[PDB]
Amino acid sequence: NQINFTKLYLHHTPAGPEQNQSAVTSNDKKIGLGCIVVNNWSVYDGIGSDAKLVAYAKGLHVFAGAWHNSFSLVFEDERLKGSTLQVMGLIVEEGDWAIVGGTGQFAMATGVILKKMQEQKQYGNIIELTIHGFCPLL
Amino acid sequence: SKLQITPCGMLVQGNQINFTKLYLHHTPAGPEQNQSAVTSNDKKIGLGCIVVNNWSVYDGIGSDAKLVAYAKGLHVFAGAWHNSFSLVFEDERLKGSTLQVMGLIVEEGDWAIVGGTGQFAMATGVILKKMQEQKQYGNIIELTIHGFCPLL
Amino acid sequence: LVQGNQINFTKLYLHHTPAGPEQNQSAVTSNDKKIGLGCIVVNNWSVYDGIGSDAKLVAYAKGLHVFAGAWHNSFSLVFEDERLKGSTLQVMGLIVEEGDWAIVGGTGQFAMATGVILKKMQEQKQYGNIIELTIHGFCPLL
Image (cartoon, rainbow over all chains, first blue to last red; front, top):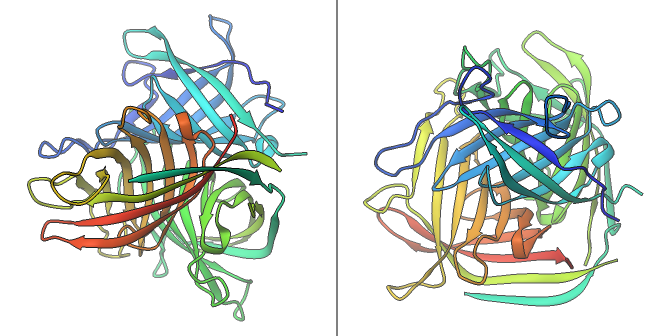
């Protein structure tokens, strides 16, 4: 039994008037790593001007040749308020992420999250999320 | 290197562990301060502060309580506090066994048990947070551990 | 019960190089002298299939470790070999040069991986050390 999730759309905005992340450390010129970025990525349930906010991706990603992410996917949805998905994995725009756990309605969750670039804007981009999660809450 | 793959089965509801009446001392200030911020929030964005924590965990409230574990890790502010730490136990019967914890919010809410080592290998579950006592230099947070350990 | 596969890695050798011309990590924050914690190091540890000059690089440990009395780790173990290219193992735990690590997830060929990673000191060098990794994990079928 797989959780029937809709495709989510993460707004990754590094700069601009709607910037939702910030770098707190920089990369060492000798090694080429070390940059840490704290992010509060907004996550919508769809595309378009009437898409509503349903979750936040609150955490950080560090650059060590590739970006290693660690964030809580906390749901602002009315029915799923409080429940979170715990995500850890490599790369922001493409690749996969691991569902290492969850809380509330998604307690003891496990699965993966597929990422796909959908739109590149001037100060950010939108990343499509496909969640293949499983919950033994039964 | 060598990678072996063996088909088998996983007993999800193998060993159920339930720890009640655990109290974490979250002390951001004072002489007993057990954490420190190493970055500050970006004044334009409103986030970025990273705090490294070594929270002590006791088996009760009062003077008869004894330290049983340390919450060693970090928590970063991105509108709320996202945690990530190893709950390493220090008592005799559980020395070495750790619980890997991730989740939002420190004072309340729920934390996710994403793994463990030693006696808590492959552990999954949740940790319930509840405000127990507010103090001058911080607060005591009651923890309620509900999880499972697969046996395989 | 859940049908799956028990994955067992042996003889993986991680290069932990804090200094030298092959340094593969860098501290970004310092320890707070008042409390005794706060040092954050971002690490890109190389993992090889053996010891010696004939060893091939098979994976990277990309993440970070913070000091709070001990070293709390969080990183992705992404493999570089052709068969496992892109697949990762999500790892969290305490101590770098010894002890146990926990497998909290995985992607690609190791989706929903759960288990532990054992560490053991092998070679102590002037600029770093080499840690042998033994992985005992489980992945559910598909």
